[PDB]
Length: 129
Ligand SMILES: Cc1cn([C@H]2C[C@H](OP(=O)(O)O)[C@@H](COP(=O)(O)O)O2)c(=O)[nH]c1=O
Ligand SMILES: [Ca+2]
Image (cartoon, rainbow, N blue to C red; front, side, top):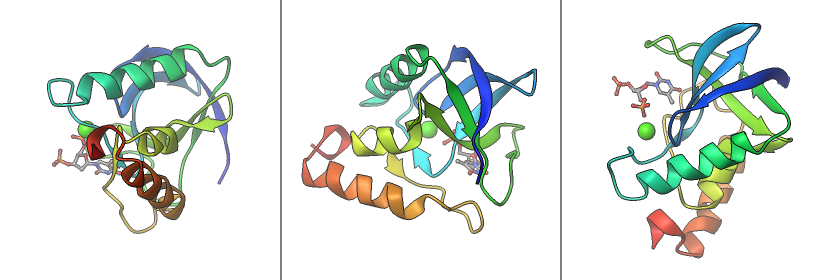
């Protein structure tokens, strides 16, 4: 897997974001996670966590996995990093997302994330409280 540059266009919610990638605007959906919807419990907290993490980053990177890079809605599917720190993992580690949508061949960081979720749940963080 390889990290590639991108720039924030606009935060959207917990697990989607509008980025410019290879010079083109594109909505990205974070791999391997599910945050609550904005109108659901912890949904505004997820949105807020992702917004700050990206808006504060001096450097955003996109990391595609081995399989599908685009979902059926045209959303880019990637691991997203903010100053070298993975947003997907950080959401899970804070109990602001569940590990989810783990499809064969786009699952490189599954075990890293499941270990974050385990710790989140142990600490009864947020969704696990
Ligand atoms: C995260 C992810 C979602 N999607 C699809 C599955 C779900 O389809 P349906 O819309 O038919 O339920 C939807 C979940 O996205 P959201 O969690 O953003 O709704 O996106 C993928 O196809 N691949 C993925 O890696
Ligand atoms: Ca969601």
